[PDB]
Image: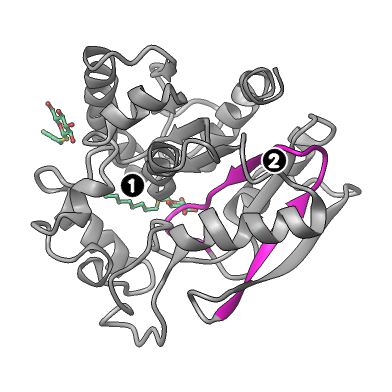
Amino acid sequence: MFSRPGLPVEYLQVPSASMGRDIKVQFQGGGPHAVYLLDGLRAQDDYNGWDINTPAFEEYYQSGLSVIMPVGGQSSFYTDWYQPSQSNGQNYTYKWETFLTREMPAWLQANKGVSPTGNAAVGLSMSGGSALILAAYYPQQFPYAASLSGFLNPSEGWWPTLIGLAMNDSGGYNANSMWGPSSDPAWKRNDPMVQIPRLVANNTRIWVYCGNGTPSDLGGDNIPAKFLEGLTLRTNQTFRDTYAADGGRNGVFNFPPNGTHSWPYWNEQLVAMKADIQHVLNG
Ligand SMILES: CCCCCCCCS[C@@H]1O[C@H](CO)[C@@H](O)[C@H](O)[C@H]1O
Ligand SMILES: CCCCCCCCS[C@@H]1O[C@H](CO)[C@@H](O)[C@H](O)[C@H]1O
C-alpha cells in the first residue's frame, strides 16, 4: 500500500519459554496501550504482513497507542497447538496463545511500560477469528478486538477441511496437530461463533469487517481473493446475526458492497478503526 519509516520502529527478540525459541517482534511505542496487529495465514519470519503490505506504522504514529507486530507463526492461527506439525518436520510445538497472553506482554511491560491490559487485538484472514477468541478468553488484556475478513465459524461444516487444506498449502502445516480432528473440542473452543456468549458477557468492543468479493480501484482483483471474501462473508453475516440475537450490543459491522481477500482493504479498515480504538482504549 506504501512503505513508511523515519519512524521509531524497533525489532525485538522476545524469548518464548513455551516454544523454546525467540520470537521476533516489530514495535512502535507511543502510549501505554497497544494495538496487537496479527498477521495472515502466510506470515513470514522476516516481517509482519502489515508492515510489508501497508503503511500501518505510519498510520498509527502519534496516535497515543503503541503498535505491536509479532513476526512468524505461518499457519499457526496464533493458538496453542496440541503437538508439533506432523508433516513438515516442525521440531517444536506452536504455543502462540501463551506467547501473546503471557510471555510477550510481560516482556513489553517490564522493559517498555506497555500495559498488559486495556489493549486491542486486530487480525485479518486467518487471525481475524484469533483476535476475537483472544478477546473472548482474555477480556482484561483485550477489551477491544477487530476481525477483518475472518473465518468466524471454523468448527462448522466444511471449514475444518478447508482450513486444513489452506494450512497444508501454506508451509505444509497439519490442522490435526493444531486442534485435532474436527470432532475435537478444540475446534469449538476456538470458534468465534460458538464463543459469542463470552464476547457478550465481557461486553467486548468488536469491529467486524468483510467485503463481498467485488474489487474496487484498491486492487486485489484476482479469483482467489474474490472467491474467498465472498465465501467467508456468509459466515460473517451469520456471526452478526447471532451476536445480535445473543444480546450483543457493542459492535461495529462493516459489510460494504466491495472488497476482496487482500491487504488494500484490510488497511482501509485499519485506518477506519483508529478513532474507534483511540476513544475506547484512551477514553
Ligand atoms: C479457510 C480459510 C482459507 C484461508 C486461505 C487464505 C489464502 C491467503 S489469504 C491471504 O493472502 C494474502 C496474500 O494475498 C496473505 O498475505 C495473507 O497472509 C493470507 O491470509
Ligand atoms: C455456490 C454455493 C456456495 C455456498 C457456500 C456456502 C458456504 C457456507 S458458509 C456458511 O454459510 C452459512 C449460510 O447460512 C452460514 O450460516 C455459516 O455461518 C457459514 O460458515
Ligand 2 in which quarter: top left
- Residue holding disc 2: 56
Q: Cβ of disc 1 within 8 Å of ligand 1?
A: yes
Asked where in the image residue 244 lies, by quadrant, the reply is top left
Residue under the point 65% across and 62% down? 47
Say which label, 1 or 2, has the lower sequence index.
2
Rendering coords of residue 214 (x, y %): 38, 26
- The magenta region covers 21-43
Secondary structure at numbered mark 2: helix
**Residue 52 visible in this rendered orientation of the protein:** yes
Q: Is residue 218 above or below residue 134?
A: above
**Residue 211 visible in this rendered orientation of the protein:** no
Rendering coords of residue 89 (x, y %): 35, 87
Q: Is residue 264 above or below residue 26?
A: above
Quarter of the figure with the N terminus:
top right
Residue under the point 15% across and 54% down? 185
Q: Residue 29 bears which disc, if any?
A: none
Q: Is residue 114 left or right of residue 88?
A: right
- Residue holding disc 1: 224
Q: Nearer the viewer, residue 221 or 242?
A: 242
Is 49 magenta? The answer is: no
